Image 1 (cartoon, rainbow, N blue to C red):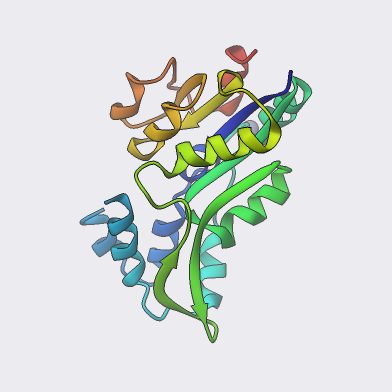
Image 2: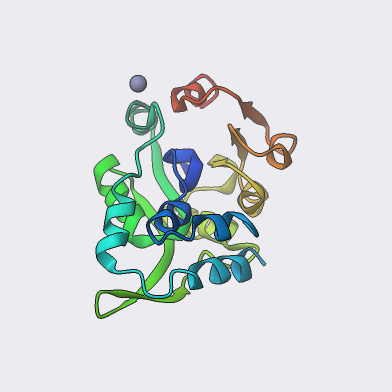
Length: 200
Ligand SMILES: [Zn+2]
């Protein structure tokens, strides 16, 4: 009976939020935080990165570090029979490196379109719509032949709600208030090993 656990990337599996890190390098991090639909908002934010040199992006994503406990938690989850996956409303260029480095089984995120080593201010992806993450959760479960009741979703905020709705077990990890009351489990200490006390 293989099970599936799906982690939100930004602020959950890693300490940072990709977009904000990439904004700081383009010096427009204040304008993006001030107007901080999820999609419409992502597109809006991305635009302010009109001609950022890929070189700068690579520099930003390098600051992305995994959340305290990530490695140990993923190791223990595999030993308990789980397929481990991550999903981001953020970007491919950052999450795929984390995926290999942490040995995740699946990784889904949006794409920062580049042209001649420069960001064209536009983005594409399957993690944009209001229900995107829940769809990703279903997709992976379907491919693995895992029943939804044997799935676990680990989120941070409002965009993780669609994922909560499809998951058998809902975990709020140092989340936004809006997510806490909706979860089955609320984790307030920033260490991913905390979930191991609750996972079957
Ligand atoms: Zn440590």
